[PDB]
Image: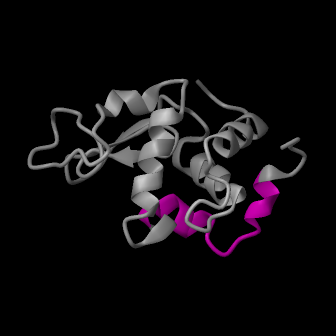
Amino acid sequence: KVFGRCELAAAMKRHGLDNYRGYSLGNWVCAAKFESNFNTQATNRNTDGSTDYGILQINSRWWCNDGRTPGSRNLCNIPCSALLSSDITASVNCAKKIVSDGNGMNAWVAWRNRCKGTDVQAWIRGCRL
């Protein structure tokens, strides 16, 4: 599913990401924009052999099982395909673990390079939230 911007904002807020671990909703919307272009089906292979999955591009080494990332963990206890659903519940639950892991949203390199330090409130402009 390709979410609209305000549609994703509303879903992320309903699932409890606004101010989760102190990150305002606009940070999460900005992260999704630059990780996946709001596309739940996005996948991207990494140099290390892992793959990133879904609207927040969650990686198969640590977080989800894709069956092809040797010596990886599955700390979110899900198949990586669960992160491609139109239902973002699994991606949000896993994102909450990742952003709690010590480096905050720096775990997302699109957030650090394109969102951190910017006017991230712009990403929720116009939305009725």
**Residue 12 at x, y = what percent?**
64, 43
- The residue drawn where x is 37% and y is 65% is 101
Q: Image check: 13 left or right of 93?
A: right
- Total marks drawn? 0
Q: Quadrant of residue 103?
A: bottom left
Q: Residue furthest left?
A: 71
In the image, residue 88 sits, relative to residue 86, either above or below, namely below
- The residue drawn where x is 58% and y is 47% is 32
Q: Quadrant of residue 2?
A: top right
- The residue drawn where x is 69% and y is 62% is 24
**Residue 16 at x, y = what percent?**
62, 48
Q: How is the image coloured?
A: one colour
In the image, residue 35 sits, relative to residue 24, either above or below, namely above
| 90 vs 108, nearest the viewer | 90
Q: Image check: 105 left or right of 7?
A: left
In the image, residue 105 sits, relative to residue 89, either above or below, namely below
Q: Image check: 77 left or right of 1?
A: left
Look at the image and say whether residue 10 sits in the magenta stretch: no
Q: Which residues are magenta?
A: 107-123
The quadrant of the rendering that contains the C terminus is top right
Q: Give the main secondary structure, helix, strand or loop, of the magenta stretch.
A: helix
Q: Quadrant of residue 122?
A: bottom right
The quadrant of the rendering that contains the N terminus is top right
**Residue 53 at x, y = what percent?**
39, 38
In the image, residue 17 sits, relative to residue 84, either above or below, namely below
Q: Image check: 29 left or right of 109?
A: right
- The residue drawn where x is 88% and y is 41% is 128
Look at the image and say whether residue 111 sits in the magenta stretch: yes
